Length: 163
Image (cartoon, rainbow, N blue to C red; front, side, top):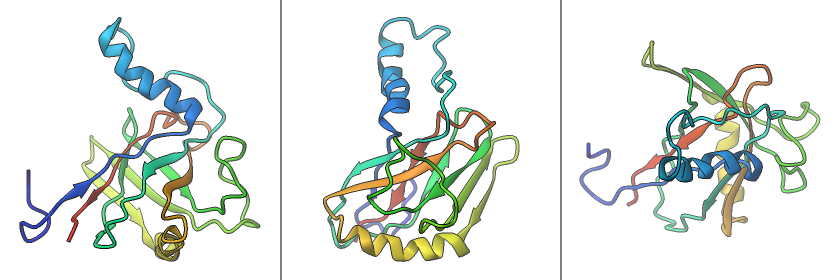
């Protein structure tokens, strides 16, 4: 319950995964209800490399979109790709550099509670957030568990301080 802002309003909303992968994450909620025994929280499914980021639009306009601490059921990192709505993470994933893609990256190691945030790329993505004001209808983005590793179980967390 740490107060990130001057004790004002705090709006922290987690972000969901691609619908297919989310099929394994939300299925997690059911895992705890039926046989949540060996059903680990992560997503033990071999998926290509695409997680969507879906969250209602926090249309506060007083929104302090600041933290994008994203995690995986395993200490590691994941890649964030900012593309247009003509690119679906479900039908596509981290595409080449021909598409507009500012690659921002977050790395969370629990054996090393250190987070490496590549912002120069996320700064360009800062401009992408303004475009959100044009997609103010919802939050949608592309993600990809680094093909070869298992973040196909990325449970993201966003801590913003609402003004």
